[PDB]
Length: 340
Ligand SMILES: CS(=O)(=O)N(CC(N)=O)C1CCCCC1
Ligand SMILES: [Cl-]
Ligand SMILES: [Cl-]
Ligand SMILES: [Cl-]
Ligand SMILES: [Cl-]
Ligand SMILES: [Mn+2]
Image (cartoon, rainbow, N blue to C red; front, side):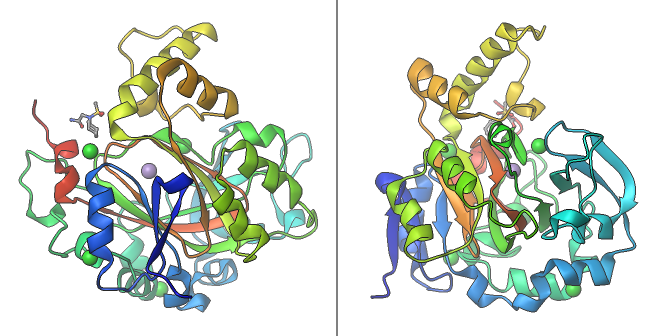
């Protein structure tokens, strides 16, 4: 039977089933006011799937100049063609190699650049914006989005959306690394998985993906989405309540000191965007500071709602294309106020 919703993270995470259901707000707003993230599945079935393929991005935009990051060591690969990234998205033997001769795990940095998404890709922009869930919250001019309505006493988000493109992490050592490191945003955001690329050549890399999800602390119902429904998993997220950010800063100041970093006692390890919380650090956060998070596996077509001020990190299981839009809900506008 079709149902309006279900629960993940043992009842702590709302999962809405129909992205275009006009009654979603009634269930959504109760969870959202308490500072929880929310998941909405099925957004891929609303989109024009031909507009979101890596081969199309390569063919249409391949000649533009970009920087990449090596996700294993944070090295920057300067001033290469965007086709050098896209043509290795799923075919492993086409990927740029490190000195060791291994194919690199790469992230495409700031592409499209700044606020240029709408100008460069007007048809993609239309397809996405017209199919975002909770549109009174997420559309540029929706009635519950205060972005366009606030004075300069509030930090206003840039014009979006922003695209996030990166390969999947592969090895046991890769389990300890992030695609995007732990950080927080002063605005709310919705992040949609529009494409998951399962590669070929080293195409049989299914079992380390399971160990990563398991060690990632994913719930039993989330593991049933793979084994029972054969949905494509993109990325493993950890999200923490805005109210726990200072306890996370205290853990990361202590670990920094243990590892011989030499940091003033007030510096901000979350703003630095330099940490990924691996299994050891997440267990220590829980045991020593009493802080619990949400471990979320974002499948193809899943939209993750991230509350303003909530620390979060992203670990790609396979190659992913994500598109995110910022918004300012009245529930969380305190997070972007420039005084007290
Ligand atoms: C110190 S901070 O965490 O960077 N911060 C203060 C601010 N004025 O932006 C806000 C960040 C969003 C959540 C509420 C706090
Ligand atoms: Cl809050
Ligand atoms: Cl376009
Ligand atoms: Cl809505
Ligand atoms: Cl990062
Ligand atoms: Mn973010």
